[PDB]
Amino acid sequence: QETVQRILLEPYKYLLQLPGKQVRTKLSQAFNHWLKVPEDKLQIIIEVTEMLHNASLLIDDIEDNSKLRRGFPVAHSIYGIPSVINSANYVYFLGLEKVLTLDHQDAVKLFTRQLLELHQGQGLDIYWRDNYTCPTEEEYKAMVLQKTGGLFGLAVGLMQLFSDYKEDLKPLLNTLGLFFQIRYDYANLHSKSFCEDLTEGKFSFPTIHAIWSRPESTQVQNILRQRTENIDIKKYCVHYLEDVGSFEYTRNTLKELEAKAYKQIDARGGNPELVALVKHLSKMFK
Amino acid sequence: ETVQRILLEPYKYLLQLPGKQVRTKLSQAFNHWLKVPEDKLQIIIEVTEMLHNASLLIDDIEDNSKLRRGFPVAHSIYGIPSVINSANYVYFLGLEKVLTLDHQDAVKLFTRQLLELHQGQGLDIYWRDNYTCPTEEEYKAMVLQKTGGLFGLAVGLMQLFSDYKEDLKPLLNTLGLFFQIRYDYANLHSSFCEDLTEGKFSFPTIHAIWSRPESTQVQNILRQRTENIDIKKYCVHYLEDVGSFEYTRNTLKELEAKAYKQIDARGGNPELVALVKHLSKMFK
Amino acid sequence: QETVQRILLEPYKYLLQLPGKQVRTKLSQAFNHWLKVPEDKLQIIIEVTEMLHNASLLIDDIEDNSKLRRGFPVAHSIYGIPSVINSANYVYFLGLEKVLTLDHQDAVKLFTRQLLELHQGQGLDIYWRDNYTCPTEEEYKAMVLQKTGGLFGLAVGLMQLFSDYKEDLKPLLNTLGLFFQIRYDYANLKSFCEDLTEGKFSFPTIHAIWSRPEVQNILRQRTENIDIKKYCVHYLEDVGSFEYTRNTLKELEAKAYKQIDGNPELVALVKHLSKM
Amino acid sequence: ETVQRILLEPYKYLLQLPGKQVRTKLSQAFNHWLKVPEDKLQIIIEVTEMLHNASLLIDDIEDNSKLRRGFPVAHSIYGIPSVINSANYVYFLGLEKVLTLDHQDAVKLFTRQLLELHQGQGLDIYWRDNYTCPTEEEYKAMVLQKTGGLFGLAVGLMQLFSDYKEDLKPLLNTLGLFFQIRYDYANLHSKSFCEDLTEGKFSFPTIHAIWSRPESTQVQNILRQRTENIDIKKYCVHYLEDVGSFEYTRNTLKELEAKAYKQIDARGGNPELVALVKHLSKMFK
Amino acid sequence: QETVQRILLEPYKYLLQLAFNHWLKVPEDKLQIIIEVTEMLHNASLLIDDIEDNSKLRRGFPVAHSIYGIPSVINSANYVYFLGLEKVLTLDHQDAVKLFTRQLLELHQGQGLDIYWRDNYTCPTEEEYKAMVLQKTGGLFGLAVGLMQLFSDYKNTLGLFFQIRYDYANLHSFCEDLTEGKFSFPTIHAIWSRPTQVQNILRQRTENIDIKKYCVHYGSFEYTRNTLKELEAKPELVALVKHLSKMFK
Amino acid sequence: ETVQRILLEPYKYLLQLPGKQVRTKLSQAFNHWLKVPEDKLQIIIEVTEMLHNASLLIDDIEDNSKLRRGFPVAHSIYGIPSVINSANYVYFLGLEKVLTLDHQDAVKLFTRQLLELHQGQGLDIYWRDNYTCPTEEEYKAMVLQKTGGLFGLAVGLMQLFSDYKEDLKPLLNTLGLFFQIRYDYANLHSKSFCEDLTEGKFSFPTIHAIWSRPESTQVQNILRQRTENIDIKKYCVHYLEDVGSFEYTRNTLKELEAKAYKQIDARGGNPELVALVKHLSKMFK
Ligand SMILES: O=P(O)(O)C(O)(Cn1ccnc1)P(=O)(O)O
Ligand SMILES: O=P(O)(O)C(O)(Cn1ccnc1)P(=O)(O)O
Ligand SMILES: O=P(O)(O)C(O)(Cn1ccnc1)P(=O)(O)O
Ligand SMILES: O=P(O)(O)C(O)(Cn1ccnc1)P(=O)(O)O
Ligand SMILES: O=P(O)(O)C(O)(Cn1ccnc1)P(=O)(O)O
Ligand SMILES: O=P(O)(O)C(O)(Cn1ccnc1)P(=O)(O)O
Ligand SMILES: [Mg+2]
Ligand SMILES: [Mg+2]
Ligand SMILES: [Mg+2]
Ligand SMILES: [Mg+2]
Ligand SMILES: [Mg+2]
Ligand SMILES: [Mg+2]
Ligand SMILES: [Mg+2]
Ligand SMILES: [Mg+2]
Ligand SMILES: [Mg+2]
Ligand SMILES: [Mg+2]
Ligand SMILES: [Mg+2]
Ligand SMILES: [Mg+2]
Ligand SMILES: [Mg+2]
Ligand SMILES: [Mg+2]
Ligand SMILES: [Mg+2]
Ligand SMILES: [Mg+2]
Ligand SMILES: [Mg+2]
Ligand SMILES: [Mg+2]
């Protein structure tokens, strides 16, 4: 009578069912080019990433109050908030249990570190959003390093524990995770489900640039406070962003991060497949 | 790194709340057999209490409560996202704090015990929100997961550091059942009948449901999630009418009896028996 | 099928459980010493009247949007509106089936007449209540004669089909069925004075509106406020629309003892029931 | 007695707005066998039209629909109490009108068949509101009672006055399931958008998805919400198509239409009815 | 730290991002104040009007209150009213203040009648309509040209209607007046020519597009042609009237 | 021209409501020094009452209050758009009544004082709706602008017509803080219920709690909620009373009253005011 496993884990399965690009899985596969972890241990780590990542996504969609993910209704929108919260937390501790494999003294300590950081960054994003105090660009980046840096750290760090590779590539991880989120944040605004970021009231990187670039106007802060689903107000806001030059700013900064991206990978070896991933991901702005 | 102050605000708010935390008093009341080293004892109490309060932060979100120990729920002030993320944060603060015990098996126990907790919680939520009332055996068996987790972490982690070898998991079972059933009964028989508004199948409502299969009112009242005082009062009168409270009391006096017997099998306890006596005064 | 009835009749059984004054069945017991209907036919008649009546209250509870019925939550508050609507309609036709006993060619005819009369009365009351046009005292009395007179007429008339008694009592049923409604509506002694919250035109409310052509607004509000209801009680109290209806109950009821003569059994019910 | 006008205002309104009125074509197409006298036939058609329209007035309250045939629901303009009482009134007016056929068996048939209607309704409402999905067999039985009731009243009341001795209960059954399953499919495959999902009612396709994939309690949950959200409804249709429920509802529909086609030959055939079933069968082409 | 001024006036400036400055004979040197003071008074009146009219958009841009929130835009707008009076304390003229107050009271009277008819569900007549419009749009015109006239010895009460152009342009962001529930001149004329349904559709305050098309169908818009070229008191102004009148052609 | 009645209907409504004459009392007690001519004084009092009540019409909209002087807000019955126009109308009716004062400085002082009122109002609204708690000093300055404006119009306008030339700005300020803090504390402490919390505005008692214990963002969050829930309000007031914010507010109130007396006596004294301020301070005994 262990159908309770299937029922308890149902919101999670639903989310996986929706196509998820699993770019991070492509990454891990292309980061074994440096790591070359035994397949048996690599499969276990990859399981922990997909589990932890999608669990964090389940929780995020509640806390971010989004309506859609990968084009399909969010898990709490169908299964109800309590079920998907508990479901996602369950997947967290299934991940820890799965990490008790590998038999490595360092896996659990690394695990707690990485999840702690993910939760700190995630908590900061919501704190700024809900307490209506915008961060500086540095604060935004530094938190993003924790927010997207968390899972990246679990993946690549867990691979480092079982590799005869001893170097220190966390610089590549920082630069990379900043490329991912800022690609996403720019991608959200520069295009139903239109400008969902504005409805969250979240401080995207572009809104942060417009907010600090022109302290003479308060609007964007106010547009964010409203949390409007109204199409016209959001269209105006992207108009404002463009007039203050923020999408341009994000392009410049994005090409910045990509330029640095190629540098410390060049210094970290060849890595052709990963570079190909990077180009493909940068294709949006051109 | 003052940022923790911000992240831990909902958790801190809940801890400010006066709660006897009698689970601590059951760790130190279970300290009569275990005689755990103090240095390890205080750190264990920290991790068990931490995990407990995180669970409560989540329960009030999932259970959609309005009040806890007389004070507004954390999400009611700080918002749902803030309290969710803070509580999940405190989970891994607990995982981190357990590593100080330096026991190779401490992490294993922490994991299994949390998985049991999440199974119990999920099961309760599944039944209530999916409108399938359980059998009394499914209720007891589940409660052992929902309430058994924290208890098992306490005594179970203490067990690694105790020269005592005997098996208290029987005593724990009886304890968790006596605790949860105590709260369910206390919740319906004393804001007022909050469990009915949650729509959850407490023990008494379950007994009424299966005892008289002819009717389906109880299920229908529960499905509503009603705040109406008149309907709620009707449900308690019907509940008393079928004798669901007499049954709940009786099973409680049953558990208390098995309790006393159980401790006596393991040596005998002056303090804990006094504790359970105090709690059993509730249905005096 | 099996157990299909248990699910469908659950609201109905729920209403039947609730302690009931069962004044219709006693008021029909009274008409036995006149009719002396055979036990075999009488039991079926009492069953059918209780059935149709209890359904009528279920629909009334929806239409009036009452919050309490016999001190216990209304059936739709527990089982939900669709469920109790369909169940109640069900017992309506179960009543028709039950009248297929008695083996009387005319029984179904009387049944049909009395039920359509009921809805005519109920529908008129609902129309005035929801469209804010107060009726004349005559329109009210005639309507109540239809509304409660419907059920009375099925009981006593169907009883008349099986009785060796050939006098007429329709004037009695007139006075009595009007006396019941004016007694109940007249009641204003929590759920206190819900009739005003319904927005219904009570007899006292009708007397108050017509006595001073210068109450309709408080009724239109349909307010649950205790203060609005209490103030409304003041405008009634100074309108004196109370002892006029109470008087009219002493007139109507007083008229009944004389119209009965005859029943002592009905007489005791009339005096006792009139104590308010 | 102009008060009947006010009492019958909701019922008159429903009769006003367009409506398939196809059931009248069913009765006509069954008189090709029954060859009922006009004097009795017109009265039976009046009784079926009345009772049907009343049942729809109540059905909207029970189903919480917003619209009928493109027009506001009766209770949305006249209010719940007014329409409830009006429809019940026309119910018993139907009883009075059937008493004019002067057949001793008509009332017994009326009571029986109306009981059938209310049992089916009660079952549909029960499963929907108490969150218990029914089996495909339970559903089919319910449809035979709910949609079978009135159709059986029409054809059976016609049967009281016909020298025809053939049995038609089998084709009645096949037809009523053709109606309910056709309407359910047409409701979900498309009017409004998936109005059945907003009711939360267990239609034929949704139950197929429920039992076909005992893994996912998604469908139960989307109905449970009674969501008006376009995105949830649209996703649910996506699921229903990927599970197979739609090809399956079609299959049972083409089977049913075929079985319809055989039972008419079993009764010698009916040109108009064959045309009716073909025309209605164009829906799932 | 006098940034509280920027904080106070932001809704106003926001509207300024977004113009008709009719020129007038015998202009005085110091008239910049008339042009500026009228600009302020107009934009403030517009901020409040967008609150009162419940508009969603202005000049293709969100309304101020949709961004800054009703209270902020209200207080800002009143603030700029009194900045207009304060700047009017310039010119050092004893009669300037009196002319200012009088004309502003006229503006508020006209507006108040408009909102009252709309919110009280009573249709206005073409007579009462023209009279009110003279106050609503005429008000600001008076501070402008009268204050300018106090410095020209060229001692004109013409009061040409603009609002009728606005009314037609709204109904010929779709049918925004119909969604507002305001009585445009065409709906008033249509209601009075053939006495019901117009009053009923307007009462709805519907955002529904289909109802709007139905209302657009109903034949009084030809009456709304009107047309007036009654200037010729005695160059640029004629060009203004010509350019604006192209709407009906 | 009966239309004026309709234009002033909201204004007339608020004036109809029974009201405290405390500001009129304040002015009548400042005439002991001012000794304004009756004829000019009466017009001054009319204009002060007008502007005050109009400002109240706007404040109830901006604070989104539900009740004023125990009776529903005017916009709740007559509607927002109507009440704004009424109040703005009353502004310039007040100015126009000041033009009868026939003094070159009357209008200049008037504009100055109205601008200050709108400066304070704006600050309150900005902090509330942008969620920026102010410092105690920023609050006091703001109170001087918002509550100080009308008082300043009063005694300043009378000072234009009084041979009294002694500096009364300090006593005015002490009065302004005394009133506003008296009102805020009175709003949160005793006797619909904690309405300020539902507004989310930073009253003095709430600000002391916010800055006194920066370790917790509760009060900022409760204010952000704008909650009508009675339980949260009761918790929050308990929180203040535990953090000691009430006691702080009382102390600043009694200090203010003391400085008041000093500043009356040091101005030649007064009998009418000394009595008024004592009566007001009995409230926080
Ligand atoms: O922007 P978010 O952080 O919410 C997101 O990137 C999700 N997420 C969650 C944690 N890290 C990233 P998404 O925009 O996909 O909803
Ligand atoms: O009944 P719950 O599980 O919600 C409860 O017992 C909390 N809880 C949750 C897990 N263990 C205990 P509480 O009655 O305290 O609301
Ligand atoms: O006042 P009502 O008509 O509703 C009433 O008399 C019920 N009723 C309904 C129809 N006939 C009688 P009751 O007081 O029982 O609620
Ligand atoms: O879905 P229902 O069965 O209620 C329906 O088919 C009506 N109905 C009522 C009885 N039988 C059928 P409709 O879709 O028209 O609302
Ligand atoms: O409709 P209104 O008259 O209010 C308007 O013309 C503005 N207005 C306000 C006063 N006078 C003119 P607009 O249509 O631009 O919103
Ligand atoms: O709190 P406010 O500042 O709005 C107030 O004091 C009104 N007010 C506004 C300006 N001056 C005083 P009230 O509490 O009476 O609503
Ligand atoms: Mg996020
Ligand atoms: Mg997200
Ligand atoms: Mg994103
Ligand atoms: Mg729980
Ligand atoms: Mg709980
Ligand atoms: Mg409990
Ligand atoms: Mg009634
Ligand atoms: Mg009733
Ligand atoms: Mg009554
Ligand atoms: Mg339906
Ligand atoms: Mg239905
Ligand atoms: Mg259908
Ligand atoms: Mg306008
Ligand atoms: Mg306007
Ligand atoms: Mg216009
Ligand atoms: Mg206020
Ligand atoms: Mg204020
Ligand atoms: Mg105040």
Image (cartoon, coloured by chain):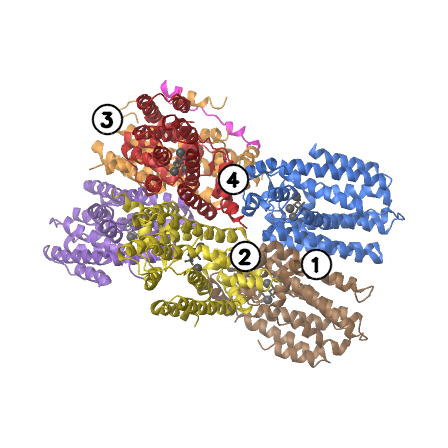
Chain colours: A red, B yellow, C brown, D blue, E orange, F purple
Q: Position of residue E205 (x, y in %)?
A: 50, 40
Q: Quadrant of ligand 18?
A: top right
Name the residue tied to disc 1: C2
Disc 3, SS: loop
Q: Position of residue C93 (x, y in %)?
A: 72, 59
Please give the chain letter of the residue carrying mark 2: B
Q: Amino acid at mark 2?
A: Pro
Label 1 residue near ligand 4, CB within 8 Å = no
Please give the chain letter of the residue carrying mark 1: C
Callouts 1 and 3 on one subunit:
no
Q: Is residue A62 visible?
A: yes
Q: Amino acid at mark 4?
A: Leu
Q: Is residue F200 visible?
A: no
Residue at 33%, 34% in the rendered image: A144
Disc 2, SS: loop
Look at the picture and state if B75 lies above or below A256: below
Name the residue tied to disc 3: E30
Identify the magenta region: E216-239
How far apart are the two marked residues, 1 and 2, measured between alpha carbons? 24 Å
* Number of the label disc, if any, that sits on residue E202: 4
Label 2 residue near ligand 10, CB within 8 Å = no
Q: Amino acid at mark 1?
A: Glu
